[PDB]
Amino acid sequence: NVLKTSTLIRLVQLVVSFVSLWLTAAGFLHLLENSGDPFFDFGNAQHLTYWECLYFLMVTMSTVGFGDIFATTVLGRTFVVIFIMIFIGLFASFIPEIAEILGKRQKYGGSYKKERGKRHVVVCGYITFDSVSNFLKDFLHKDREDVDVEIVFLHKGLPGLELEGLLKRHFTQVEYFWGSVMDANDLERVKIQEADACLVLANKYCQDPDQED
Amino acid sequence: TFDDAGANVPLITELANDSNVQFLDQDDDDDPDTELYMTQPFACGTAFAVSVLDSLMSTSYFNDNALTLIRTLITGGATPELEQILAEGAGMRGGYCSPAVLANRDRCRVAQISLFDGPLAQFGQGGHYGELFVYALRHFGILCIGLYRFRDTNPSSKRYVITNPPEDFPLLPTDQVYVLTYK
Ligand SMILES: [Ca+2]
Ligand SMILES: [Mg+2]
Image (tube, rainbow over all chains, first blue to last red):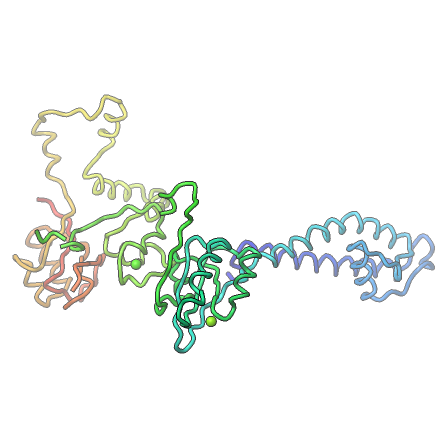
């Protein structure tokens, strides 16, 4: 029961399919080139290692094709032609789908580590660069008395690059987590048992204010 | 409040999404990954959802007769005849009726009764469920099927279901018992 999710199933299928076919095809070329061709009484042959064949198949399926190593038997060349027609499609589709699955990962997971004597405020609801910048410039304003309150944003989304820059400018006193106040697990992550308050911001410019309320 | 009682009033809530059961009550110790049937609001009978019924496909296959047992009870005694009369599109036809069809009034129903007072109170006073079952069946034809017990014993009004307890299961004077009954 270990391979629990559709993306982990697809990931392990892609990786092990690729590696097993690549290792297999490298053994097949190694057989043909070191055999030599039967039409020439096995006189036309190359003494490639398996590792040179494995490298040469990677260099050809990626379409780099250095030609430091190449097949010279008619069987190894016809195998390379068949391999090119098949494995360029595999490489060009598999490597982007691996990169997509590795890219689709939560970057603001994890948990608020409550410092020994500081207070914190949880903030949620309509969290965006426009709402957060207007909130922080009033909340952290120098005309207020100096108080060490951490702000902990909780939102079901990735920050845009403008907001991620703003969060990094306030790194000492502002933290952000992926999640929703609708989940008890996310409320525990933000440590809301011992937050000083929770602020629920509203989208004042929503298409309908009753769905927002 | 009605001081002119709040949470003392009994509710049953139909839920469109079983995950929303966690919002129905306080000090439940909610988790997102418990199945609906384990949650405190369902265990108390304060919540219901369609997701508990879909095994009636497999029970209808494995024992058709047992689905008619549930329905006789759950519909209060609807029949293929009544279903056909409604499917005739005329609406529910009725009137005065014969002694022959009125015989169907003498049929079993589910009822709930208390061990606080009356003849069965002797079992609530530190007896066991097996003693209660045999006594009620012998003296009254009352067939006990489970308990509805206060969750906490001391201050809340909430109670929970206990389907078919063991014979040596200890009773409390505050318990109520679910019974199949004929009058
Ligand atoms: Ca709750
Ligand atoms: Mg901090």
